[PDB]
Length: 46
Ligand SMILES: [Zn+2]
Image (cartoon, rainbow, N blue to C red):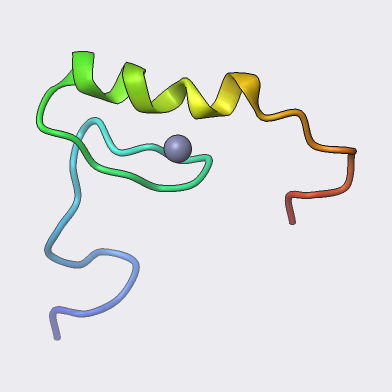
């Protein structure tokens, strides 16, 4: 009915790498930061 890929709780500024919503675009940035310093060995995603 109202459950699945398309549910009730999606934001236009929700991270995709990890997934984190925020009240405002500007805010998102601050978060996206964690996706800059993080220095993974290699095979992480997937
Ligand atoms: Zn993220």
